[PDB]
Image 1 (tube, each protein chain N blue to C red):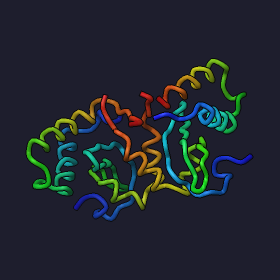
Image 2: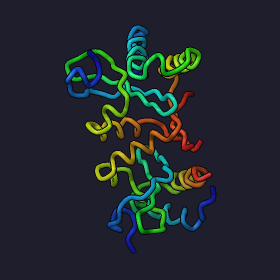
Image 3: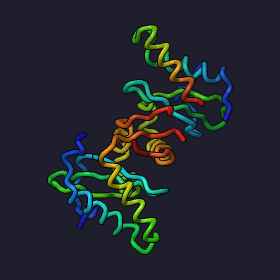
Length: 64
Length: 63
Length: 41
Length: 52
């Protein structure tokens, strides 16, 4: 059965992410649904840009 | 006159620095050799894809 | 800070389905899978 | 390491941009000093984004 954007639901929260070489996956929840999905960042870039940017803002960007 | 006030298109996002809740992007503009500090709120709406692409270029560790 | 393992294994499956199991070697997958699990910690 | 070709004078201008934006009376001076020290360090060493 469908997962990711294919659920046709609206993005709820971005919980977490994981980088794999050049691939970045986001772990997300949808409104009205309880499941947690891995979604490639390319699949949500254009639908949810400000939510994705706000998620990155919430992270600690640091050195070294 | 600097930042979005130059009225130039964004060229490249070079760097960023975070101060508590304030995130600044350091950017260049098309046709201009200067580097400007710009608060992410000033470019968030106009250049979201470039911003996201810049973050993608960083290494997101476990730690 | 606890997320059910089954839910994490679903997400890993999502990732395999996007990338394709034939797109990486088995140790590449195995090292990435450990990275995937540690990143939930 | 593309950042290495960036001049000190350029970083100071960018700092002045941050100050013009927030600006100077919005933090204590020792708050500013610590942020400034981390601002200079941020150009020199590679960044990690930390899932919090």
